[PDB]
Image (cartoon, rainbow over all chains, first blue to last red; front, side, top):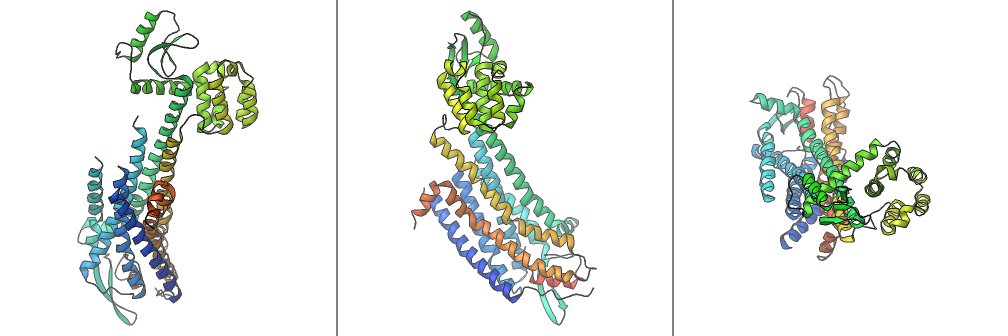
Length: 452
Length: 21
């Protein structure tokens, strides 16, 4: 029951925090305002625009009122402001985390493809509704503490509803799981799906160059009837048997000629089969496992051309690839019958093993658009590091604080500083979204520099 | 912030100085 003195907020920390707050404020105001002007002048545009609105709203609602409450240590306004400021704050936070998830999913759907403004209204409606409990639980109370008479605006311990009484006690867990863990989980999930989708896209362009793509049944360089991307339909010399097997292969024959999308589906079947056969092979699985995503596709390319058995014959080269001896395996593969028979395909594949990149196949325009989206996902990394100090502070208050442990005043003193730091970090994220997007997108960088 | 009860004036003074979150 005794105490140490939790007025805390050393007069020295008040200067540092309020200077950091002013820097983040104007830079966040300027940064998000000029971002909105670029969007309103020139799909992903509106999602970034909604994010900047949530950023701008979060800056103006969460920075000044906490700067005042730090220096003045008082709530001068009425009960409406006590119920309005937290309500607007949790609405802007919801808009921000939902815009990021809608933005990440948008990048996944943009790559997997081979009702946007509706989500905005859905985001803002859901963000407001989920923030409503803040406008009901907050209220103004007074007390005679120490030698003064204070007027406090807080989340009331007593509520007129069993649901609100639960929200008053478990608010920080609801914020930590929904406004932090859930976006991190959703984003990391669709980022993983996007990279796996970009990988099966590159292996398509890779094989399309080395094997070609034909929408009608054709005869191969060896002389066998083939369609799609090197999809063997039959090894029989009868052209009539090829048409019969082709119609039996698809299940819905358009007389023997297909489109681009049908061949892509056929191609993905063969890649899945090639991956399964490699994993079932005791010679190929250990080498395939040690390889990166790029060199995995180079091995799948060889399995596409020579089958699992033929690739397994490169005993010396496979061991070199497993031991990451790229140049030694390149020289060894060049001495093969495979290199002599198909030099163009072999030289590109060998180069891919040698350099570990897609440089021999993909064009630079596609290479640039991919690296933008993949790196632009760093907005969630900044989101995770900026909102962690504030969330960690509220978690520690629900974990370490015990009324019966008398040295707790030293703890509340520490939490006051961590709370005002976390409120600056969470606002710096709204301030860093234009800075990070400017430094990353390159296109946005030239649009930013066009101002001044 | 919030407190277990208004009888904990040390916690209520904490929310007096605490951020509005």
